[PDB]
Length: 303
Ligand SMILES: [Zn+2]
Ligand SMILES: [Zn+2]
Ligand SMILES: [Zn+2]
Ligand SMILES: [Zn+2]
Ligand SMILES: [Zn+2]
Image 1 (spheres, rainbow, N blue to C red):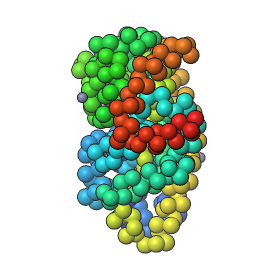
Image 2: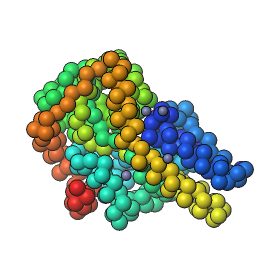
Image 3: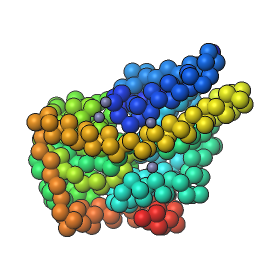
């Protein structure tokens, strides 16, 4: 059979982990003996920084990186990293589905990559070993970020010291004090046990963690036309399922963190959240030139 390896860096009981397994389940039912899907979670095949290499060589067929991890291949996806750009997952969804949002799926056409769809995870929450209620609370802390210039600027804006790290290394980074805070949707906190080394989690919803499911164009366009049709339709069905259940998964993980009895959850007043917004929103100006001032304008319209 045609082998499709789906590699990713998250745990199985997460939006992306379930999505990859659902894709395997449906494809193997619909193309019996014609296509086999092998899923490699938790960086078990390829980890951060290395997966793009594998995809373009042909060592893996589908990956789904965070939208924040494409700056070296395109400058447009950085729009999803801008803090407080989207108020909720609804706005995110509306932008992704617009003509401009869909054109971004081909933003890496030149580099031999085909965008198959957007998968949601959820809004990011701040965590640290001290309560983060107001921007000043972050001063002097070391925060792990994904490999994004936008996210680095976000923390520099609150006088924190950002450190780019691969996802697989974050728990150890926090436990050893190399970093002392980070940002993550609830599901990544719980599934990587980061609540065990982060005493305070602030429900900031200050940015979005979402993915682009991608493949190698030469591989994908090289498939038998009939097989590709079924795979594309099946991926679209999986996207629906992932996206409808992501928020609920994250809420389940928030509750599992509460039940774990390791951390305290800080709720922000609308006013406190407005303070974070005022401190971080100036980062948008630094990236308008690369992203496109008009592209950013449309994203606001989605709100
Ligand atoms: Zn379950
Ligand atoms: Zn959606
Ligand atoms: Zn850095
Ligand atoms: Zn379902
Ligand atoms: Zn759950």
